[PDB]
Image (cartoon, rainbow, N blue to C red):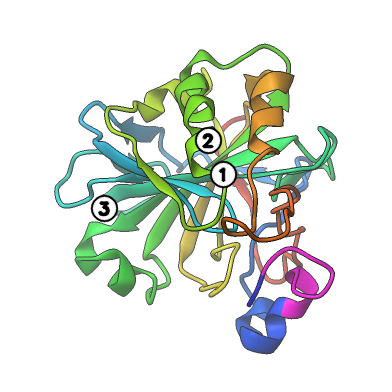
Amino acid sequence: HWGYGKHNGPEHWHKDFPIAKGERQSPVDIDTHTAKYDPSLKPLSVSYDQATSLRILNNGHAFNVEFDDSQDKAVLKGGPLDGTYRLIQFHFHWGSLDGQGSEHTVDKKKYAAELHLVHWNTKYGDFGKAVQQPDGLAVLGIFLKVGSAKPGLQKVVDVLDSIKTKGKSADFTNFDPRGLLPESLDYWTYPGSLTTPPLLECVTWIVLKEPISVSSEQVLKFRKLNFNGEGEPEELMVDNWRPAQPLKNRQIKASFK
């Protein structure tokens, strides 16, 4: 099945998922000189005070921090969005080395990692219905650079030993995603897709300009995870990023001057 290797990685995905070659694929390179400031864009509203994390999962690609999305508890609104988008999960993409790992790039710069906070449009009732709609999802993307530790990440890092291999999960309650956000909510936005199969073209991307800092030790713990299941040949979970895809007929807009 799909993955990140030589035989199953991104260049192969189109054979099982032909939208991989579609008109609105993600990620993309953000050319900061050509992204236009759009004064009609609103501030983003991130309301995570009542978020209820439940569980962390190793799905064999990344790890997912899952939320209770059965009410309006953790919502994204504003920005480029019409209506209300509910947080369902977050996950990361990262590299084997600090010089790669992000999916989006900024003037071709790759960050060490990228965090995706995934939210679905409440007007479609559930996540599975939302992904079938062009405005079904809003994903908040946040770059990670290596420097000072991010204290709000350490609880995640802590737990990874318990979910080393594919198919392992653990209780992960009371985790506050606010501790993963940068100071500024300035962003770029464009229409795109999920960055893993099924690659559905259902996402309004909101990519924050300001990266977070994490420590080398934090990232090194991500790189000890495994893509394999228990008791299978070890293959370190690294380089689980899709490269930039063609922008095609899209505009990237900036919330800031």
Question: What residue is pinned by disc 3?
Answer: 83
Q: Main secondary structure of the magenta part?
A: loop
Which residue is more in the foreground, 60 or 119? 60
Question: What residue is pinned by disc 2?
Answer: 160
Neighbor class of circle 2 (other Cα within 10 Å; few <14, some 14-19, many 20+) is many
Counting every numbered tag in the picture gives 3
Question: What residue is rendered at 39% in x and 65% in y?
Answer: 135
Question: What residue is rendered at 26% in x and 53% in y?
Answer: 83
Residue range corresponding to the magenta coloring = 3-12
Q: CA distance from mark 3 to mark 2?
A: 35 Å
Q: Position of residue 60 (x, y in %)?
A: 57, 58
Q: Position of residue 82 (x, y in %)?
A: 31, 54
Residue depth check, mark 3 versus mark 2: number of the one nearer the observer: 2
Q: CA distance from mark 3 to mark 1?
A: 38 Å
Q: In the image, is 50 to the left or to the right of 26?
A: left
Quarter assignment of residue 7: bottom right
